[PDB]
Length: 385
Ligand SMILES: [Mg+2]
Image (cartoon, rainbow, N blue to C red; front, side, top):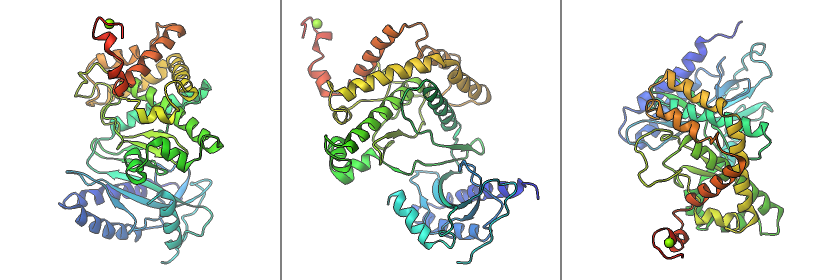
């Protein structure tokens, strides 16, 4: 029995077909009801010789818990999120399809699904998640994912301890795809809404006090991820940054999501911004303030990260150029997109100049901080303060 492709195609198509039927429904409530029925049907055919390509390890799909999926918010479309139970195997080509067994945080979902699943006792059981978008073009997300992976590889190679979290994208059609969500994390919006704390106070409560290893560890993770995404947002010109599309994980890292406006995507910023990455007071406070060692570390990481990126520039630009040749995406706008991208690597600068640039960029990223208004008047008047 060779690895047959038709089962897999039918599986992927079934997920898209579900989305299409949900999209005929006006209300979220109705889509939720329909989704339960749809997933129950899917389970008729499982386990099967099919896989979720976003897994990143060989496995068979065994179950899609039909009550546990989520219809996501959409004005027009019908995006949805499913949890998918799989059994890991070492080699998919040699492994037989598993025999059927008859019938909040990530951590609680995993617990509840495992307990309710006839497969949940198996040691090779794993829960995966995927967002199915049957009417959204994900090629721009895929480009971002490819670039993020490349930057991650560059920083690893150059031993720069920046941290980012590329999330997997599958492009199905020109107007459909799949996204592996980042599950161990909540938007900063919700972290603040639920806790009613600043991020600093949240860290002190959740991780520990200033003298604790946990606090320092979380702070280090926050800085390394902040620096990583600062560079990502600058190089890719990621726009539409807000607390709804920045997540916080249980380790203190931030994760940027939703790359719907990158590179030359309209509308262009008219406020002379170097990047839409904004370093708020709240963020600077987590780093222990403007004069703090962790803020200095942040700036050092930005410089070492940019040095590393610059050194391997062609690896990143090539990814963008290949995507541009194949596709007519909104983030491309004729010649200038690539020119401007290359210029953001600062190939002509010395490391001394790059250090000065990082200072300017960091200063600019805090432009929304009220202190900058208060203490910026020397640039706007003939006074020296
Ligand atoms: Mg002046």
